[PDB]
């Protein structure tokens, strides 16, 4: 009856997944949405380093083991929703610009951004990424896993019982967790996607404690606000 957690997915069943890495170490999730662009949380950009070669890993299942599918590209420029510095609070959404477009095979595909589709609370969604299962684990998950979640209601998520206004869940964010209203995925899950009913809806917002009742996960919703932003960077490109 009790006991419940995530499960490791079928190797390379999420061809769009990407690992953001500093010095070869995974720090966040991301979603390839165009040959030379990754979408991830902005929290995921370590600012206290001019070094630590930032790299993106695609077509991977195991963060450790070698793989005929893996592709390591280099970040050309981080495009965060904030300008230079600004307020490193809300708007936890970022665009990673790669040095070269990535080879597209069956283990490495793109995921499309949501459009007209909306997201009602109560929906069963799935989070994908490399987040550890031990609240104390100092290392992320080796294999790529997946957890099921339920979109909580803002009214209930903004209650005194939950975040109670701090952070306040605006119209662009969304909550999700188990019946205990808590977050499953732990270390290294930030940046991953929130796919519901087969539609890429949001981005896992980083910087939140895992395993605490009434403290669900926050997600950045791909609202018109960010579609616009996305479209401008990716369109127009640099062809001409």
Image: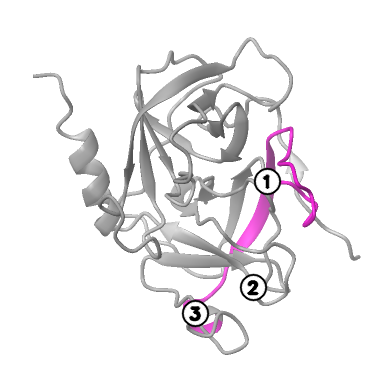
Q: Are marks 3 and 1 in contact (CB under 8 Å)?
A: no
Q: Which residue is mark 2?
A: 215
Determine which quarter of the picture holds residue 220. bottom left
Alpha carbon of mark 3 to alpha carbon of mark 2: how far? 11 Å
Locate residue 211 relative to residue 173 in the image: left or right: right
Q: CA distance from mark 1 to mark 2?
A: 17 Å
Name the residue rendered at 35%, 18% in the picture: 101
Compare marks 3 and 1 and give the one earlier in the sequence. 1
Question: Could you tell me which secondary element the residue under label 3 belongs to?
Answer: loop
Q: Are marks 3 and 2 in contact (CB under 8 Å)?
A: no
Which residue carries the number 3 mark? 166
Residue stretch rendered in magenta on the structure: 132-156
* In front of the other: 132 or 9: 132
Residue 199 image offset from top left, x and y in percent:
46, 47
Give percent across and percent down for residue 146.
68, 44
Quadrant of residue 173 within the rendered picture = bottom left
* x, y percent for residue 9: 71, 35
N-term mark: 1 or 2: 1
Up/down of 180 relative to 95, above or below: below
| Quadrant holding the C terminus | top left
Residue visible at 74% across and 33% down in the picture: 142
Residue 7: quarter of image: top right
Asked if residue 61 can be seen in this view, the reply is yes
Residue underneath mark 1? 131
Callout count:
3
Q: Are marks 1 and 2 in contact (CB under 8 Å)?
A: no
């Amino acid at each position: 009856m009790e006991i419940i957690g995530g499960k490791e997915v079928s190797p390379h069943s999420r061809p769009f997944m990407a690992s953001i890495q500093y010095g070869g170490h995974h720090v966040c999730g991301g979603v390839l949405i165009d040959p030379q662009w990754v979408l991830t949380a902005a929290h995921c950009q370590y600012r206290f380093t001019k070094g630590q070669s930032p790299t993106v890993v695609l077509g991977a299942h195991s963060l450790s083991k070698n793989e005929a599918s893996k592709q390591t590209l280099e970040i050309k420029k981080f495009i965060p929703f904030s300008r230079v510095t600004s307020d490193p609070q809300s708007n936890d959404i970022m665009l990673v610009k790669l040095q070269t477009a990535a080879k597209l095979n069956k283990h490495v595909k793109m995921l499309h951004i949501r459009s007209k589709t909306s997201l009602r609370s109560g929906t069963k969604c799935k989070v994908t990424g490399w987040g550890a299962t031990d609240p104390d684990s100092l290392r992320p998950s080796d294999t790529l896993r997946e957890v099921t979640v339920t979109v909580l209601s803002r009214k209930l998520c903004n209650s005194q019982s939950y975040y109670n206004g701090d952070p306040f869940i605006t119209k662009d964010m969304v909550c999700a967790g188990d019946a205990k209203g808590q977050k499953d995925s732990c270390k290294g899950d930030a940046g991953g996607p929130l796919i519901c009913k087969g539609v890429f809806h949001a981005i896992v917002s980083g910087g939140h404690e895992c395993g605490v009742a009434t403290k669900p996960g926050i997600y950045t919703l791909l609202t018109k606000k960010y579609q616009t932003w996305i479209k401008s960077n990716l369109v127009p490109p640099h062809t001409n």
